[PDB]
Length: 383
Image 1 (cartoon, rainbow, N blue to C red):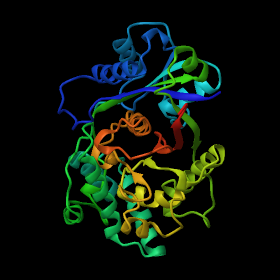
Image 2 (cartoon, one colour; image 1 turned 30 degrees about the vertical axis):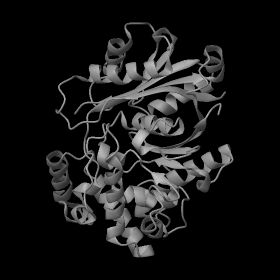
Image 3 (cartoon, one colour; image 1 turned 180 degrees about the vertical axis):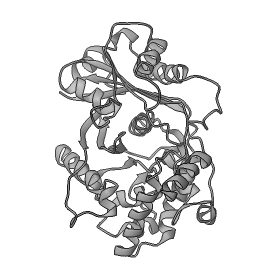
């Protein structure tokens, strides 16, 4: 059963506390935008998949009833206790592909040892969207990459530089200013080579997408905006031995690798066919290694990809035309849906000053709560 994204919407992603509204109004802004984009009645929504991290188990329902009105539809919380976190989009896709609904709303929102203690305080005071282990794990993985392949600390700063430069054209991004490479390098130290401008900040915001079956799209004449999910794969923790483990593997390198390989196989495409990417750059180090995990270049060649400008406009792949988590900030529940919104706009040729000319195949890379990796390929459903 083919599955399509037929409307998308988001709020601006803002510094926590910059905007004086509660999570239900954020959800309403994103949700109502997505429904208006889709051009459908609210009653067409048969289930809602809702992604958020903080608050109790009723926040999903509270957000949906405020956005759509009260109904008896199922409201599924993506983040449960006794399973690894999914994503709103992966779950919505599952409901459609398995025949449990013809049309669904995916919605996400968020409203905010000596070294672990030190990182905990730093994350709080610098407003980073990270758990205390994360900067250390991603720094270790980047250092490991430098040791094996000769990547330079400036390559990681260049990735971050590139994300901030893209952000200048995204009005939904918390940060929309270009910093110099020198400013990236000189910003406050977080861990090792990682500096503040290489780490994703917290943002408050919401995102939403309407997902629909092939028959729903045909029945309602919605072919024009229908972006097809041509492949989507999730990989949860891979269990390995002491001898095979590495810092790169510990932050999900092989999970991304396998998820993407399986997408490529399903869709019958290769990395070189992808035109535009939105990936999970929680740290610059995760983006750099993810270039190789996705198969964009051979192992150890990310520094060359970076120095050629093959991650930006005029290069082979335009990566994070949004500015990335690094510029947008990371409202935990909403991040994946914002990536989706941008890639759908790119493929629909509605991305304005960020438009990748002639984009036809888009790749999303996202991480769930708990660390599961989701890779998704999109193309226009009926070009």
